[PDB]
Image (tube, rainbow, N blue to C red):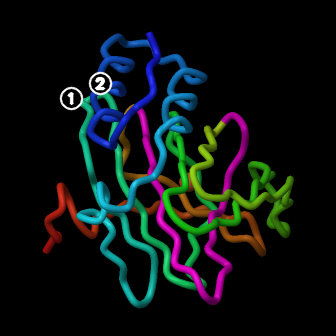
Amino acid sequence: ELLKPRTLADLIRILHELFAGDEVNVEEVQAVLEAYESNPAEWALYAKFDQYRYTRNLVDQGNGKFNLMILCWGEGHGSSIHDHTDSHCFLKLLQGNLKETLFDWPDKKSNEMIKKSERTLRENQCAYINDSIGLHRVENVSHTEPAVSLHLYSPPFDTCHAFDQRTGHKNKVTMTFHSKFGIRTP
Ligand SMILES: [Fe+2]
């Protein structure tokens, strides 16, 4: 039974329930993420920005079944073109806007990567990506407003691949956290 999360903590409890089995209902997860209304007071603990690039801040480990984390994007910060290691990935905006660009999996030949589409994700919107759909890049193109987003990955993964736009070549990347449970990482 899907109910509206009243708070971030409530969202987390609902997610534990949803992920209690070994099979995940993606539509239900997206729906509950969208129904959570961003309340900056509830996630301030996790919103730790960096001057130079975006930060990843772990919120919950999902009793093993998922990682839930908050990403903080300064003006002009963006990500690489990346995959998600055969996991489910959900992204919800908690503050500001992000441009999401979708790319096709590259061919064998070196070649400018092909942009499928792009869209602006606005506050409280929740999107879904998985490798079968394609690859993506996420960016805060604003010059005046920092952005904050909530991400959920299941199963959790800490390694993925980044892709070069000019050539399609991929490189392995290990994901790092800037903070976990509100505490900065060494
Ligand atoms: Fe992503």
Residue 63: image tag: 1
From where the camera sits, is residue 113 visible? yes
Find ligand 1 in the image and state its quadrant. bottom right
Residue 16: image tag: 2
Look at 26% across and 33% down and name the residue there: 62
Instruction: Identify whether 39 is placed above or below 35.
Output: below
Which residue type carries mark 2?
Answer: His
Instruction: Identify whether 159 is placed above or below 66.
Output: below
Please, what secondary structure does the residue beneath circle 1 have? helix
Q: Quadrant of the N terminus?
A: top left
Q: Where is residue 93, by image quadrant? A: bottom right
Q: Which of 160 and 129 is in front in this view?
A: 129
Which residue type carries mark 1?
Answer: Asn
Query: What is the distance, in whole Å, between disc 1 and disc 2 at their CAs?
Result: 7 Å
Q: Residues within 10 Å of mark 2 (few under 14, many from 20)?
A: some
- Provide the residue span drawn in magenta: 132-154
Q: Do the residues labelled 1 and 2 touch (CB within 8 Å)?
A: yes
Whichever of callouts 1 and 2 sits on the residue coming sooner in the sequence is 2
Q: Based on the picture, tell me whether residue 170 belongs to the magenta stretch.
A: no
Query: Residue 71: horizontal and vertical position, in percent?
Result: 42, 63
From where the camera sits, is residue 87 visible? no
Whether label 1 lies within 8 Å of ligand 1 gets the answer no
Instruction: Identify whether 10 is placed above or below 134.
Output: above
Query: Residue 169: horizontal and vertical position, in percent?
Result: 67, 65
Instruction: Identify whether 107 is placed above or below 153.
Output: below
Q: Which of 121 and 156 is in front in this view?
A: 121
Please, what secondary structure does the residue beneath circle 2 have? helix
Look at 57% across and 81% down and name the residue there: 145
Look at 31% across and 28% down and name the residue there: 65
Left or right side of 68 for 101:
right
Query: Residue 92: horizontal and vertical position, in percent?
Result: 54, 49
